[PDB]
Image (tube, rainbow, N blue to C red):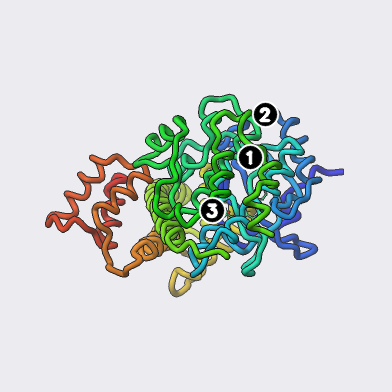
């Protein structure tokens, strides 16, 4: 029997997004039609921490585990360059994106969410699997239904793969990490700490450990001190504060277990009178919008650098291929050159096999406006393959800007820039410098186009 090839069984439909350790692609079984979400981990870009057999055994165990609040794993594939982890697709998106879209949110809603998280974590810990990187974006809703169950993603991965050091991969990690993880000695209790921070945020909309940039946040976490002095804590039950305290207990051996947290009075009472936590929802909407804009700004700048890189690479490849020196290539040649560009850049999970490349080239060749067959001008192909991506990138940045601009003022204040660039970990003096060069009127605010220009100048343009 043959070692099984991922693309012999699955075809890619669309990219779902970048997650921790790699892109996730919506795929479909070629025989049965079953849709699945495939996390593809690039061996070049993600180092392993364990030996192959340690990884294999963990995969085999994960395939046997089943819990309603844990992502289901079906299959695992490995080739020369990649690991392919095939799991169930969930369509309800990230929890915090659902929450900001409601008018009411109470401790009852929070308790129901936390109970699910604790139930998942408890099961995973019984089986000796630790998350380590638990955060709001690892909490997916199963479907778009109002009542939908939460599915936790990424259990087991941090044990086997090294985290990215790149800030586009790191936004938001610092708030949630347990202090003991920072110093190196940690166990499954780190996941209770993370859950405690999530709960604190659900009930007030502010992180318990906060600060102006990543390192400032880590400094607060490492000291471990936090308060309930914010006004919005006055609407909150004492039993919720007690559970939080126990979850954010500094010494792990004295911190409550996941299982014990399920039996806590707060969970028992509030999942079995209650105002809406309106101020919390407001603060969550603002926190989420700020996080998503910082992320969008990082992705935009990274996409601009990737485009400078790939544009020149792709031109050199076609120039080499163009044996007539006449600037003309056929479809097969554009395909082979676009393939060679993948034979190095292992960024594009969605170009999974030759068929997906064929399709993408054809979108551009269709897109070559009007079509002459045989003599494609490769310089114009490069422009449109890359302008497509550039246009897409600009539109994604803009969506995030608009969502952040909740008053529809059209502008972001310099106070708000400071918050965004802090979260993006862009140097204060450096963005102020680029703001001076763009804002020569001391308006102390920027419109979208001005913001986009600042980003271009912060990535060498
Ligand atoms: C935006 C996104 C990156 O969270 C997208 N995303 N990420 C995942 C996701 C997340 C993690 C996944 N982990 C897997 O295996 C690891 C061994 C456990 C396998 C598939 C995984 C998929 C996901 C999903 N399943 N359904 C829907 N959206 C999903």
Q: Bin the neighbour count of mark 3 within 10 Å (Cα to Cα): few under 14, some 14-19, many 20 and up.
A: few
- Residue name at image x 59 percent, y 24 percent: 185
- Residue 203, percent across and down? 50, 54
* Secondary structure of the residue carrying numbered label 1: loop
Q: Secondary structure at mark 3?
A: loop
Q: CA distance from mark 1 to mark 2?
A: 16 Å
Earlier in the chain: of badge 2 and badge 3, it is: 2
Circle number at residue 237? 3
Query: Which residue is disc 2 drawn over?
Result: 50
| In the image: residue 6, left or right of residue 423 | right
Query: Which residue is pictured at 38% across the width and 59% down the height?
Result: 397
In the image, 50: left or right of 232? right
Percent coordinates x, y for residue 20 in the rendering: 56, 45
Q: In this rendering, is residue 63 above or below 398? A: above
Q: Between residues 228 and 439, which one lies in front from this camera angle?
A: 228
| Percent position of residue 268, x then y | 68, 53
Q: Is residue 186 above or below residue 263?
A: above
Of label 3 and label 1, which has the lower sequence position?
1
């Amino acid at each position: 029997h043959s070692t099984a090839i991922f693309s012999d069984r699955y075809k890619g439909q669309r990219v779902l997004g970048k997650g921790s350790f790699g892109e996730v692609i919506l795929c479909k079984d070629k025989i049965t039609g079953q849709e699945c979400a495939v996390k593809v981990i690039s061996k070049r870009q993600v180092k392993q921490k364990t030996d192959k057999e340690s990884l294999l055994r963990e995969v085999q165990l994960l395939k046997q585990l089943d819990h309603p609040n844990i992502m289901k794993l079906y299959e695992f594939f490995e080739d020369k360059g990649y690991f392919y982890l095939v799991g169930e697709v969930y369509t309800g998106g990230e929890l915090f994106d659902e929450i900001i879209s409601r008018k009411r949110f109470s401790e009852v809603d929070a308790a129901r969410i936390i109970r699910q998280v604790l139930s998942g974590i408890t099961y995973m810990h019984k089986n000796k699997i630790v998350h380590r990187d638990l955060k709001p974006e690892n909490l997916l809703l199963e479907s778009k239904s109002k009542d939908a169950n939460i599915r936790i993603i990424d259990f087991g991965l941090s044990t086997h793969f090294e985290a990215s050091k790149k800030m586009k991969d790191k936004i938001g990690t610092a708030y949630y990490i347990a202090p003991e993880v920072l110093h190196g000695t940690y166990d499954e209790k780190c996941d209770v700490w993370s859950t405690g921070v999530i709960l604190y945020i659900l009930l007030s909309g502010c992180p318990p450990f906060n600060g102006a940039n990543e390192y400032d946040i880590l400094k607060k976490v490492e000291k471990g001190k936090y308060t309930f002095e914010l006004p919005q804590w006055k609407k909150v039950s004492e039993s919720a504060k007690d559970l939080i305290r126990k979850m954010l207990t500094y010494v792990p051996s004295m911190r409550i277990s996941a299982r014990d947290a399920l039996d806590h009075e707060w969970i028992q009472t509030y999942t079995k009178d209650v105002p809406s936590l309106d101020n919390a929802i407001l603060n969550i909407r603002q926190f989420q919008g700020t996080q998503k804009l910082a992320q969008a700004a990082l992705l935009y700048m990274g996409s601009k650098l990737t485009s400078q890189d790939e544009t020149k690479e792709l031109t050199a490849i076609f120039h080499k291929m163009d044996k007539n020196g006449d600037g003309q290539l056929d479809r097969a040649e554009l395909i082979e050159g676009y393939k060679e560009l993948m034979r190095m850049k292992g960024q594009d999970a969605s170009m999974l096999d030759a068929s997906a490349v064929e399709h993408e080239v054809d979108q551009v060749l269709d897109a070559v406006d009007f079509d002459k067959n045989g003599y494609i001008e490769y310089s114009e192909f490069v422009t449109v393959a890359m302008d497509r991506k550039t246009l897409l990138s600009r539109e994604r940045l803009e969506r995030a800007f608009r969502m952040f601009d909740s008053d529809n003022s059209g502008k972001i204040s310099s106070t708000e820039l400071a918050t965004i660039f802090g979260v993006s970990d862009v140097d204060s003096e450096t963005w102020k410098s680029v703001l001076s060069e763009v804002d020569k009127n001391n308006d102390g605010e920027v419109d979208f186009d001005e913001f986009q220009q600042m980003l271009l100048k912060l990535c060498g343009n």
